[PDB]
Image (spheres, helix red, strand yellow):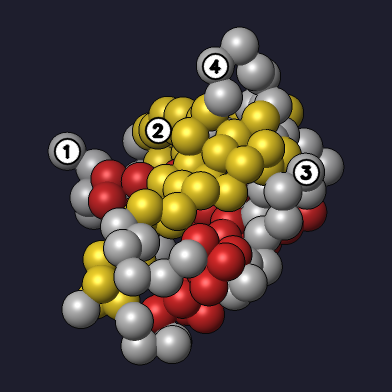
Amino acid sequence: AMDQYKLSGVEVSGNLAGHSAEIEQLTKIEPGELYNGTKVTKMEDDIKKLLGRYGYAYPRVQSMPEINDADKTVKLRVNVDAGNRFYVRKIRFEGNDTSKDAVLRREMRQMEGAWLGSDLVDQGKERLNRLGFFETVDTDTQRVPGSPDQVDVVYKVKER
């Protein structure tokens, strides 16, 4: 296997949605960093999370090791596809048995008709968590059928 080799670099290409600089930062190598499958998926996951902050809800990242035996190093060839950028059509609430939807909507930071922003969906979640009513608060981003660029954000809530 390759867990003993050193990462010589990460070469990224594809459709980066204008975020090549940030994706380069994420992609830089650490001192004496070894090749590792797990850190590779963690890297793919970090890239998707980043693009998600910009409304690219379903981005792809594939990556392929190029072993160089002369150097005992491995280079990561990486393809990024940001995919469609989504805006929010509807924000929806569930589990919501005591309080009018108004009580939750009022805490949103992600607005209908705006570009989707995972951090915005998250802030909504923390504002929800923070008023005590709920045991759990989870979010789901659902594509609107027939739509290439619309999602609904569902806040699934469970009261105490």
Residue 107 visible (yes or no) = yes
Above or below: residue 27 compared with residue 120: above
**Mark 2 or mark 3, which has the lower sequence index?**
2
Query: How far apart, in angstroms, are the residues tagged by discs 3 and 4?
Result: 16 Å
- Cα–Cα span, label 2 and label 3: 41 Å
**Mark 1–mark 3 CB contact (< 8 Å):** no
Local crowd at mark 4 within 10 Å, few (<14), some, or many (≥20)?
few
Numbered disc 4: secondary structure: loop
Residue 104's place in the image compared with 8, above or below, is below
Could you tell which of marks 1 and 4 lies nearer the N-terminus? 1
Q: Which kind of residue does numbered mark 2 sit on? A: Pro
Q: Amino acid at mark 1?
A: Ala
* Label disc, if present, on residue 113 of the rendered structure: 3
Q: CA distance from mark 1 to mark 2?
A: 12 Å
Q: CA distance from mark 4 to mark 2?
A: 37 Å
Going from N to C along the chain, the mark reached first, 3 or 4, is 3
Label pair 1/4, CB-CB below 8 angstroms: no
Residue at x-position 67% and y-position 68%: 109
Q: Which residue is mark 2?
A: 65
Residue 11 is drawn in which quadrant? Answer: top right
Q: Could you say which disc has been placed on residue 1 in the image?
A: 1
- Foreground pick, 123 / 37: 123
Quadrant location of residue 25? bottom right
> x, y (%) of residue 97?
31, 63
> Where residue 153 sits in the image (x, y, percent)?
53, 46
Q: Is residue 66 visible?
A: no
Out of 29 and 42, give the one closest to the viewer: 42
